[PDB]
């Protein structure tokens, strides 16, 4: 924890935009798929 | 001893004993020993056995034998084919540096005093100039002594000496954005008549490692052979000779660590068109054997050259803070203030030559002043205070052995040798050294 | 990523599960088949051979 | 599988990452 | 004998390790776990120095015609040339040797 | 002690030899070229602190020229870096002919070789230091010589203890003998009048008085025997009263 | 306080310090402080570790270079020969007597030594005078008939 | 001082009562000496800076060093006539105000001391605590000769766990990945350009060790954080038992008495905490938590 | 017969490396004994005694001249008390607690 906080501090302080300051991409339930769930079988439900 | 004539000492075997004892002591200190390369062949020529004067049976050549042995101890046993051409070239440069150090301090102090008496002269004459400079602030403006990348070199300074660059004053810190390369170690240029794509390094380290000629150094070089190829003495042009002005542009990466040469461009753009790019040589020694004369066609070469053949090549915007210092021979010298590794208020870089007024106006998009005071460089940041070329020579000349593996000639061993905390032997922190 | 991060967390878990379960199931299958064939190898008739002559059995197992 | 099923089936395969995920779960909840 | 049994160390050999030995001494040194036996702890440098101590212990004196390295005369003659050779710093190091 | 341009600037506190009256100087120059300190005459009374050893203010007080000045002494300078006091006889020049007022409130005061011969600042003088430049010219000084050129013209060859004949300069002390860290404090008897007169050593068993006692302590080793055989060095115990016995040792 | 002032040089009576001017400002500008929190005086970046740069207050009696290079290297060799003996890329926990208790074949190291340390010496000794080679010979052998 | 004496006494007792390891008092005092030199290195430059206090309306201007050394007193001449006493009390109040300011900064830097020393004792408690073999029980459990009975009050605690049940995740890994993200960055488009920007040169300087020239003070290279896995490192009791059992018994005896007294500290801090928030009573009423044993 | 040492915590094997050496070899006017008398949890006199032996180990290892006035500058109180003890009871040497 505290070591990543050291990282985050450096990045947010000086402008190093990779890794922990860069927002991880989440996948969205697709516009068609009426599925409310995360499915390992099914990729096209989760859209970016 | 078993001999009636020879004296019971064998300096060859004693020196071999000394080497083996050095190796033995290091095996004891470290527990292992770097296997001296297959290039490590002891030279023993300098060693000479004793000479015993007959009428007295006392030695004749005792200091002789001794200096032979000590030379053979100093000399490591491996020739050039062990060392990378980078190793070799840096080494030759360090050697030459400590060769000229005496003359360097000589000429540098002489030159410092000439510029100083220039100061004393402007201050003394005329009587009206003295009556203006009577004031302490005025005179301390008039000129300031400041460490140069060589040594303590006085800087001119004034409102009128600094306005031509547009400088407010020496105590005015200013940021800037500038043109540089997106990778200076990677400078590309295609020579038209040549059509060979040279990838240069414009970084001053390898700019020197081939003889000191840094990027932007403006030079004159000379020729020894006949450009008409004619041995005959009737009508010859190059026996009279030509003097080729040039400018350094870096190190071309060929494909052999040794066989790169120094890259420099004709400043006469006519010949930059027709004759083409000139390489300098695989080293300092190389360029100097290659060229009868190489000289900086300016005094001092602090004049820093724009690179036009790379003008299009320089596409990076460098965000560089700095602080004015002085203008010596009409060329600005500044004090940059951001350096890598100095995160305190001491580490202001030394006085650096920046190009002339034209180069300020051209390559300097932004130069926005402030107000500040001259903070001299600190010890570690001062180069002639930190020029470690000598220990560098020792470093490289013992570089190979570090590449070979360590094994314990006391064989069968496993335990890692327990070195102890804070031992003055193992202390490496050189916080100020 | 700041209101609903756990979405990316679950995404990573599904990534791991996908790139894991088949060498994982593979290991599980190999191991269970190993222990089962050990059980049956003990239950075999070589048990009866050993029971009727042990020293021979250790001899031949040490030999081959 | 669905997510809950991935959990319930890896919970017999990889003790570690499942114990891990269940902890991250309890903590992001009680946050 | 001195050069041999002191300064010619390479002519000394250690107990050559087995590989279960190598790996296990690594494993119980680079992390000292709970409940270790006392058999994993005798280091090779302590072993070299104990072997040299045994060398100096079993050095014997007598006429060298027998299996002896040297006589009292040979040894104290070397001692005398040396103790005459000793300078200041040599004598500092020697008297510290005596003192410790 | 600092240089701004190589020239050294020391911080010191000039003091009357009794350290009663003192006057500090922030950053003064160190010129290893004038063999005497030249302080302004105004301090001849600030540091005249009439003690008893020096009836009047100073000890020596002589009208000198360089007559401009009063050469006075001895005044106890103390430089910030050094722990040894540096006692001088400074020239006390007047501020008239020699207006030492260089700038606004500055002074142009310089520390002399008369001092640098007493400070650890002297080591900056032998070639390699920060004052070997500023040293005046003479045949034993090559001005701009490489320091290594001087060391090797004197006889530098290798590192420190590079060649394995010269011992290591850090096995020079393989043991510090600090008695209460190692085996306790010696048992210290004396034979004489005092600790400082008599000697560490009792009289060995060979004395004329001890041989009957040693003979008895040999044959009847289990009864207690009268005699002087005890005041000897040879004792019945496994432990003989030979000096520097560590009487509180954990394991004797 | 009375003597803190004395050693502080007495009260310097400067007329009109906190007395304000008609326009509400003070005459005789006040005294201004230059104090803050020092931002570069962590003692750890100072009294650091001697050979590495892990700047803190923990003692760690390290291991010499070489006696860690060779050490860890032959540990890797011994593990690659014990646990993964048949070289199929698989770690067999049950190697043979010969694999578990065979010392590695890295005694080619002393052979490398024999080629690049002692061998050039053995060429170099073609210049020593025989009586010394024979003397150091018999001396390192221990067979020296010095006629008493 | 006793903050860090209490802290390291409790850490000593920890690394022993949580693992059969002993800290070498050589180290125990190298820690406190590093905190003391922390304070000396603060006090050094604190004595090159000033705090200015001023008495009524600013008539007396007291110039001081934050440690409390009165350097100057500029006075208004309407104060020379107060008295000898009231002059004293007024310059004393001006001193006192300046002291308040200097001690304000003094406490603003003692928190920096707390924090550097904390970054210091990090890898040690992280050593004892962020290892697979680190576990406690609930403080209410009647620890019995063979284990730990249960609590009765405040059912269902929330047992945390600071460690990934997955494979090992250590700070050296995190920092090596930190430099790799840093690397990929200084390769990336925003990377290489921000690096030529001030925001990048500033970071490079204030955080680039491997760029300190030959001579500069500070970390002269990059350092991974420290690793002291206690339950997998016999610290000193090995050396003590080898050399002499007497020192062993007493060194472990101190570490144990130290943890015992840090326990007594938690006990009395809790005791006041309860007499504060109404849990406990000012004189024993509940004996059967002592008399039924 | 030399196998135990009283006070087994501060051994001598860990003082042959000068504690914070290159910090008081860098300004030994800024580094009195009182800055490092925290490094050892021993009695005060013995701690100063360790410190002077330490500066000696350090100067020896840098191969520079020691300052033989360091014992005096650490035990100044004791130094002047010996001087006045001598001047009072006319002896030479060092005063022992029996004469206080």
Image (cartoon, rainbow, N blue to C red):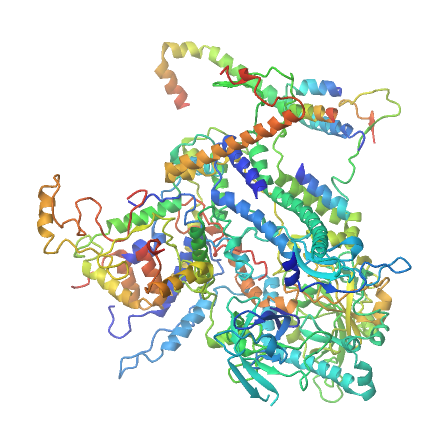
In the rendered structure, the answer to whether residue F128 lies left or right of residue H201 reads left
Residue lying farthest to the right in this orientation: G23
Q: Is residue H231 above or below residue B109?
A: above
In the rendered structure, the answer to whether residue B228 lies left or right of residue F193 reads right
Count every numbered label the image shows and give the total.
0
In depth, the one of I65 and F91 nearer the eye is F91
In depth, the one of B209 and F97 nearer the eye is F97
Task: Report whether residue H197 is seen.
Answer: no
**Quarter location, residue B301:** bottom right
In depth, the one of F178 and C61 nearer the eye is F178
Question: Dividing the image into 4 quarters, which one contains the N terminus of chain I?
Answer: top left
Task: Report whether residue H79 is seen.
Answer: yes
**Quarter location, residue B181:** bottom right
In the rendered structure, the answer to whether residue C41 lies left or right of residue H220 reads left
Q: Is residue B71 above or below residue G68?
A: below
Percent across and percent down for residue F175 are 38, 54
Question: Dividing the image into 4 quarters, which one contains the C terminus of chain I?
Answer: bottom left
The residue located at (34%, 64%) in the rendering is: E90
Q: Is residue B117 above or below residue B387?
A: below
The residue located at (44%, 62%) in the rendering is: I72
**Quarter location, residue A26:** top right
Percent across and percent down for residue G62 are 50, 47
Percent across and percent down for residue B228 are 75, 81
In the rendered structure, the answer to whether residue E38 lies left or right of residue H282 reads left
Percent across and percent down for residue H194 are 79, 51
């Amino acid at each position: 924890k505290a070591e990543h906080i050291e990282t985050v501090e450096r990045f947010k302080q000086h402008g190093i935009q990779v890794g922990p300051v860069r927002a991880p991409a989440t996948g969205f339930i697709a516009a068609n798929s009426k599925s409310l769930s995360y499915f390992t079988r099914r990729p096209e439900e989760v859209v970016y | 001893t078993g001999e009636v004539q020879k004296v019971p000492f064998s300096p060859l075997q004693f020196r071999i004993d000394m080497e083996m004892n050095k190796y033995r002591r290091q095996q004891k200190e470290e527990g292992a020993v770097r296997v001296p390369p297959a290039m490590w062949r002891i030279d023993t020529s300098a060693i000479v056995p004793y000479k015993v004067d007959p009428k007295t049976k006392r030695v004749i050549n005792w200091r002789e034998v001794k200096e032979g042995i000590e030379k053979s101890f100093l000399s490591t046993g491996l020739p050039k084919e062990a060392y990378t051409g980078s190793e070799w070239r840096e080494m030759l440069h360090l050697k030459s540096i400590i060769a000229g150090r005496a003359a360097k301090a000589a000429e540098l102090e002489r030159r410092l005093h000439t510029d100083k008496v220039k100061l004393l002269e402007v201050s003394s004459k005329s009587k009206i100039a003295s009556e203006t400079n009577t004031s302490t602030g005025s005179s301390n403006s008039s000129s300031i002594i400041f460490p140069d990348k060589d040594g303590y070199h006085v800087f001119d300074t004034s409102v009128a000496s600094l306005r031509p660059f547009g400088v407010s004053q020496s105590g005015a810190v200013f940021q800037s954005v500038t043109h540089t390369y997106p990778s200076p170690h990677a400078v590309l240029y295609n020579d038209p008549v040549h059509g060979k794509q040279f990838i240069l390094d414009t970084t001053n380290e390898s700019c020197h490692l081939f003889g000191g000629f840094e990027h932007g150094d403006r030079l004159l070089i000379r020729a020894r052979k006949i450009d008409k190829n004619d041995n005959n003495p009737n009508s010859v042009l190059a026996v009279k000779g030509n003097e080729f002005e040039v400018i350094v542009v870096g190190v071309n990466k060929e494909g052999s660590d040794s066989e790169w040469q120094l890259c420099a461009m004709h400043v006469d753009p006519a010949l930059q068109r027709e004759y083409g790019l000139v390489f300098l040589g695989t080293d300092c020694v190389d360029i100097h054997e290659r060229w009868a004369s190489v000289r900086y066609a300016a005094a001092a070469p602090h004049v820093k050259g724009r690179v036009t053949l790379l003008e299009e090549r320089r596409t990076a915007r460098e965000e560089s803070l700095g602080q004015i210092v002085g203008v010596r021979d009409g060329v600005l010298f500044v004090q940059w203030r951001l350096l890598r590794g100095g995160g305190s208020e001491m580490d202001r870089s030394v006085a650096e030559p920046i190009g002339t007024v034209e180069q300020v106006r051209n390559a300097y998009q932004i130069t926005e002043q402030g107000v500040e005071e001259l903070m001299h460089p600190p010890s570690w940041r001062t180069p002639f205070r930190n020029d470690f070329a000598e220990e560098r020579l020792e470093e490289l000349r013992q570089a190979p052995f570090k590449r070979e593996n360590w094994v314990s000639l006391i064989q069968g061993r496993y335990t890692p040798k327990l070195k102890r905390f804070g031992y003055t032997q193992h202390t490496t922190m050189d916080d100020f050294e | 990523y700041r209101t609903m991060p756990m979405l990316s967390f679950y995404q990573r878990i599904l990534k791991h599960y996908s790139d894991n379960v088949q060498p994982l199931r593979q290991k599980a299958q190999n191991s269970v088949r190993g222990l089962a064939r050990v059980l049956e190898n003990e239950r075999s008739a070589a048990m009866e051979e050993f029971r009727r002559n042990s020293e021979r059995y250790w001899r031949n197992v040490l030999e081959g | 599988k669905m997510m809950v099923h991935v959990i319930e089936e890896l919970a017999l395969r990889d003790d570690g990452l499942v114990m891990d995920i269940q902890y991250i779960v309890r903590e992001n909840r009680r946050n | 004998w001195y050069l041999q049994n002191i300064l010619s160390v390479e002519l000394l050999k250690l107990p050559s390790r087995t590989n279960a030995e190598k790996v296990a001494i690594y494993r119980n040194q680079k992390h000292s776990l709970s409940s270790k036996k006392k058999g994993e702890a005798a280091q090779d440098d302590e072993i070299l120095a104990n072997i040299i101590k045994e060398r100096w212990r079993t050095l014997e004196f007598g006429d060298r015609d027998a299996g002896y390295p040297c006589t009292f005369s040979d040894y104290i003659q070397f001692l005398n040339e040396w103790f005459k050779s000793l300078d200041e710093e040599g004598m500092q190091r020697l008297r510290e040797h005596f003192d410790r | 002690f600092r240089m701004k341009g190589g020239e050294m600037f020391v911080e010191y506190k000039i003091m009357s030899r009794d350290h009663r009256r003192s006057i500090r100087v922030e950053d003064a120059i160190v010129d290893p070229s004038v063999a005497r300190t030249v302080v302004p005459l105004s301090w001849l009374e600030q540091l005249r602190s009439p003690s008893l050893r020096l009836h009047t203010g100073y000890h020596m007080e002589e009208a000198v020229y360089v007559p401009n000045a009063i050469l006075a002494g001895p005044v106890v300078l103390s430089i910030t870096g050094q722990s040894v006091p540096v006692v001088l006889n400074p020239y006390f020049v007047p501020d008239d002919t020699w207006g030492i007022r260089r700038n606004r409130d500055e002074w142009d005061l310089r520390l002399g070789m008369d001092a640098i011969e007493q400070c650890t600042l002297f080591s900056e003088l032998r070639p390699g230091g920060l004052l070997y430049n500023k040293l005046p010219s003479s045949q034993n000084v090559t001005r701009h010589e490489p320091v290594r050129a001087t060391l090797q013209r004197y006889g530098m060859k290798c590192g420190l203890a590079e060649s394995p004949l010269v011992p290591r300069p850090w096995t020079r002390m393989r043991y510090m003998f600090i008695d209460e860290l190692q085996r306790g404090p010696k048992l210290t008897e004396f034979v004489g009048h005092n600790p400082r007169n008599g000697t560490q050593w009792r009289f060995s068993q060979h004395s004329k008085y001890f041989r009957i006692g040693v003979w008895r302590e040999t044959i009847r080793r289990n009864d207690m025997n009268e005699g002087l055989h005890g005041h000897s060095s040879w004792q019945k115990s496994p432990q003989q009263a030979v000096p520097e016995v560590r009487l509180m040792a954990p394991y004797p | 306080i009375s003597d803190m002032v004395e050693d502080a040089g007495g009260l310097e009576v400067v007329p009109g310090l906190g007395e304000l001017d008609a326009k509400g400002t003070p005459v005789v500008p006040p005294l201004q402080s230059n104090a803050h929190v020092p931002q570069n005086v962590s003692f750890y970046e100072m009294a650091r570790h001697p050979w590495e740069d892990a700047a803190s207050s923990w003692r760690r009696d390290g291991f010499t270079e070489g006696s860690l290079a060779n050490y860890e290297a032959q540990y890797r060799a011994a593990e690659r020969a014990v646990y993964d003996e048949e070289g199929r890329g698989g770690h067999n926990y049950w190697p043979s007597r010969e694999a578990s208790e065979g010392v590695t074949s890295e005694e080619k190291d002393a052979a490398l030594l024999r080629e690049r340390l002692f061998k050039p010496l053995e060429e170099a000794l073609s210049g020593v005078e025989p009586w010394a080679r024979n003397l150091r010979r018999s001396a390192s052998d221990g067979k020296l008939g010095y006629k008493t | 001082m006793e903050v860090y004496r209490r802290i390291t006494e409790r850490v000593r007792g920890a690394l022993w009562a949580h693992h059969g390891r002993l800290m070498s008092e050589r180290q125990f005092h190298r820690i406190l000496a590093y905190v003391y030199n922390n304070k000396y290195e603060h006090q050094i430059r604190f004595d090159r800076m000033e705090v200015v206090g001023r008495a009524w309306e600013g008539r007396v201007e007291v110039v001081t060093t934050p440690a409390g050394y009165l350097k100057r007193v500029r006075v208004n001449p309407c104060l020379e006539e107060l008295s000898s006493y009231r002059q004293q009390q007024l310059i004393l109040a001006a001193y006192a105000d300046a002291c308040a300011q200097g001690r304000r900064l003094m406490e603003k830097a003692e928190i920096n001391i707390y924090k550097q020393f904390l970054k210091d004792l990090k890898p040690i408690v992280m050593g004892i605590r962020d290892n697979p073999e680190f576990y406690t029980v609930p403080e209410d459990s009647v620890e019995t000769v063979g284990g730990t009975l249960h609590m009765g009050q405040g059912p269902t605690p929330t047992t945390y766990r600071t460690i990934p049940a997955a494979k090992a995740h250590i700070p050296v890994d995190e920092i090596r990945a930190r430099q790799e993200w840093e690397k990929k960055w200084l390769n990336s488009p925003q990377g290489q350009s921000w690096a030529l920007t001030l925001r990048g040169k500033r970071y490079f300087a204030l955080h680039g060790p491997q760029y300190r020239p030959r001579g500069a003070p500070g970390a002269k290279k990059v350092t991974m954080p420290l690793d002291l896995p206690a339950p997998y490192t016999s610290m000193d009791e090995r050396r003590l038992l080898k050399k002499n059992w007497m020192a062993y018994l007493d060194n472990k005896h101190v570490a144990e008495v130290m943890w015992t007294r840090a326990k007594i500290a938690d006990r009395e801090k809790l005791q006041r905490r309860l007499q504060e928030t109404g849990q406990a009573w000012h004189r024993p009423i509940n004996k059967e938590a002592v008399s039924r044993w | 017969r030399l196998r135990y040492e009283i006070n087994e915590d501060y051994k001598v094997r860990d003082e042959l490396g000068p504690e914070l050496f290159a910090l008081w070899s860098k300004a030994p006017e800024r580094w009195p004994p009182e800055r490092l008398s925290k490094m050892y949890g021993l009695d005060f006199t013995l701690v100063r005694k360790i410190l002077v032996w330490h500066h000696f180990k350090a100067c020896y290892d840098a191969c520079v001249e020691p300052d033989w006035t360091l014992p005096k500058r650490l035990f100044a109180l004791e130094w002047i008390r010996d001087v006045r003890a001598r001047k009072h009871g006319l002896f030479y040497g060092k005063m022992r607690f029996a004469e206080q």
